[PDB]
Image: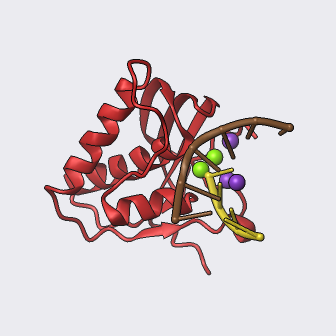
Chain colours: A red, B yellow, C brown
RNA sequence: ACAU
DNA sequence: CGATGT
């Protein structure tokens, strides 16, 4: 502890897992929604959590912001650190879009730099992350 | 077991 | 109850 209020918080939302995936990023302090991705017909929770972090990195870099990013996903934080999303989702025609976006996010990480700290949101101590979809 |  | 991940 405690919370770094000057930060961006991201989270996935889904209808099924695998299922329809979306994500958004919010100002941790105010809850203002700063970006939201159009729903992707089939993906996993972790692919969406990964895309949300990478989108946050790109969003902050474009704006010359040094704010950290909070995610509640141990998995996605590791995938970003590794620059590799180790998803089990079948690659087929139905999953082509999510896998294209994941491939492109990895490619961005491999061609750009950033100093953005990627921090674990401590849900057990602080409650749900401010970007949560409220579906659980 | 832990994190979603 | 089901699923995705380390
Ligand atoms: K939720
Ligand atoms: K959670
Ligand atoms: K499990
Ligand atoms: Mg989450
Ligand atoms: Mg959530």
The answer to whether residue A8 is seen in the rendering is: no
> Which percent across, then down, holds residue A71?
52, 58
In this rendering, the count of numbered labels is 0
The furthest residue to the bottom: A1
The furthest residue to the left: A111
Quadrant of the image containing the N terminus of chain A = bottom right
Indicate left or right for A79 with A20 as reference. left
* Vertical order, A33 against A40 (above or below): below
Residue occupying the point 70% across, 40% down: A134
The answer to whether residue A44 is seen in the rendering is: yes
Q: Nearer the viewer, residue A1 or A103?
A: A103
Examine the image and state in which quarter residue A124 appears.
bottom right
Q: Nearer the viewer, residue A66 or A49?
A: A49
Q: Nearer the viewer, residue A94 or A21?
A: A94
> Which percent across, then down, holds residue C6?
52, 65
Examine the image and state in which quarter residue A6 appears.
bottom left
Indicate left or right for A65 with A88 as reference. left
> Which percent across, then down, holds residue A43?
49, 32
Indicate left or right for A90 with A58 as reference. right
Residue occupying the point 51% across, 72% down: A4
Residue occupying the point 48% across, 41% down: A48
Indicate left or right for B3 with A78 as reference. right
Residue occupying the point 34% across, 64% down: A82
> Which percent across, then down, holds residue A23?
49, 38
């Amino acid at each position: 502890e405690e919370i770094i209020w000057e930060s961006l918080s991201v989270d996935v939302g889904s209808q099924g897992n695998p299922g329809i995936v979306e994500y958004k990023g919010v100002d941790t302090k105010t809850g203002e929604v700063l970006f939201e991705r159009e729903p992707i017909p089939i993906g996993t929770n972790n692919m969406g959590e990964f895309l949300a972090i990478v989108h946050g990195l790109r969003y902050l870099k474009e704006r010359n912001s040094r704010k950290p990013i909070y995610s509640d996903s141990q998995t996605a934080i590791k995938w970003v650190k590794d620059k590799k999303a180790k998803s089990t989702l079948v690659r087929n025609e139905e999953t082509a879009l999510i896998w294209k976006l994941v491939d492109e996010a990895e490619e961005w990480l491999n061609t750009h730099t950033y100093e953005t700290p990627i921090l674990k949101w401590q849900t057990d101590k602080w409650g749900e992350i401010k970007a949560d979809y409220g579906r659980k």
